[PDB]
Amino acid sequence: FNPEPITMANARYVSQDVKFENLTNQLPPPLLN
Amino acid sequence: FNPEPITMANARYVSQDVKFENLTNQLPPPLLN
Ligand SMILES: *[C@@H]1O[C@H](CO)[C@@H](O)[C@H](O)[C@H]1NC(C)=O
Ligand SMILES: *[C@@H]1O[C@H](CO)[C@@H](O)[C@H](O)[C@H]1NC(C)=O
Image (cartoon, rainbow over all chains, first blue to last red; front, side, top):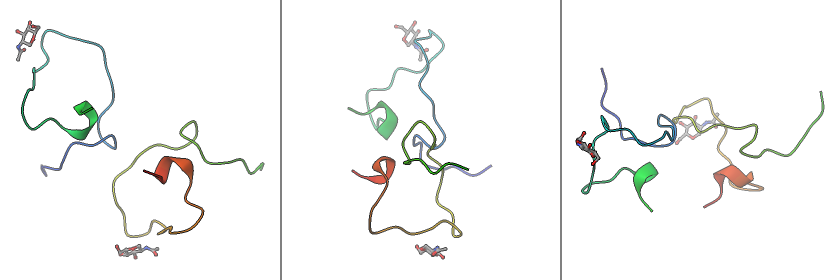
């Protein structure tokens, strides 16, 4: 257990899913335009 | 053995490490902003 910032080093792009959280604040850089 | 240019087709983003090289010149295209 070690909380780290979310980047493309540990995230991958996937398709839309209804279990996925819908974020409008503090978007991680992968999810930020 | 066949040296080819470094691109995103053969490189993946990883987290910071102390044994990684520190590049300031001729940065590969994945490492330019
Ligand atoms: C996120 O959005 C999808 C599509 O609107 C919705 O089905 C789902 O209930 C929402 N909530 C979360 C956080 O899963
Ligand atoms: C790269 O730079 C960092 C300082 O941010 C240093 O800790 C590390 O040893 C350097 N790596 C090499 C192999 O030069």
